[PDB]
Image 1: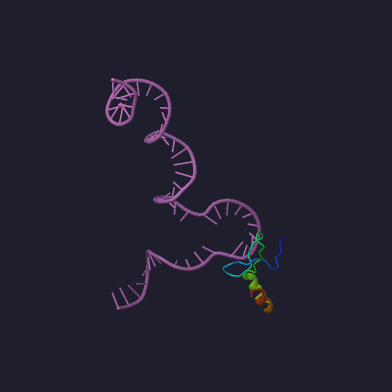
Image 2: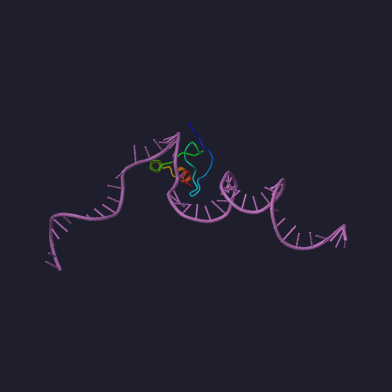
Length: 50
DNA sequence: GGGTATTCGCCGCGTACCTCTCCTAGCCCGCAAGTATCCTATTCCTTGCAGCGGT
């Protein structure tokens, strides 16, 4: 069981770290982006990767 | 030249997460530490020159 709201940030590319050791967040993988595009949902996707 | 066959080389092969370990090799030069050696004294003996009483 794990959670993250606002923690650290990677260095080269500003994205949340990964893994439970560091306080990282989950990964909104490619297939999930496809899935969100399949709905009419556009605002949520745009915010979720911007 | 030309239509064809055969070979060569490049491109590709699922998502998300958890645990662990390990991450250049070799030379070189200053440098700390530890040591064997060399000069430093003391005691005995036998010389060589300058003062010195004595007449």
